[PDB]
Length: 10
Length: 276
Ligand SMILES: CCCCNc1cc(C)nc2nc(Nc3cc(Cl)ccc3C)nn12
Image 1 (tube, rainbow over the protein chains, first blue to last red):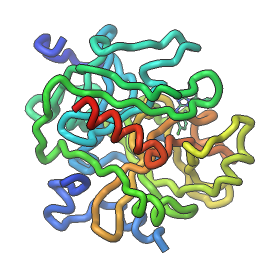
Image 2: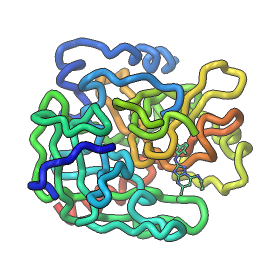
Image 3: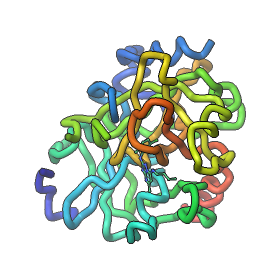
């Protein structure tokens, strides 16, 4: 249930 | 400037349980942490699927300390590399992207102790992680100190209490926010007599005896996290251990085992100055 982290880090 | 928290020591404010630690210098059953109470706490986050891997700690603007078994453990086919992970610093909430507060960093290189013993008892369960670029410190991000021989000698004693933090399991549901618990260091003999596992000098155990009434322990998800103590000499926080392993969580007659950070400091220095 983790919140989407910015794609800039992925 | 390590070990002095922006929201506490630097403002001369005490957190609600540090007095318990100082008074002894003669996560299961823990409580919610206060904001900025452990600015060195790091979360190891897996990219795909998005998930919490382990705890870790910030020891400088470029390095993170954690347990080797969080990255490499052949028995469960666990073998992560730089690009499989993300390091999240300055957090409080386990699942939310705390915008404007936390910092997410990429890894440049992972260093596992050459003699880490995953085959038998997790001896030398320690690893360093070099971030791609320095993290800027703030009210919620600040490194913890590594012990010097003297500090280690006077604080690492049976009866003395340390503090463990983590987002791991609350029972052998996960917490909403960082949890904290203060535990007493246990005499080597008692540690040895509580398990079948061969215990080495690079470990120490902590927890309350079944008769002491109080309880608490680390659990799955907490591994790699810091066991810290506050020095009564210079008021700074020092990381004395790394959450390593335990047989179950908060079981009576059982204790958590931690990697003895000072015993491996030579390797830590070696890796740091030889690589940045
Ligand atoms: C030497 C074998 C120990 C078996 N228990 C294990 C095995 C492995 C691989 N990883 C493990 N991580 C943990 N977490 C942990 C740490 C403490 Cl401080 C207390 C209770 C637990 C849960 N326990 N644990």
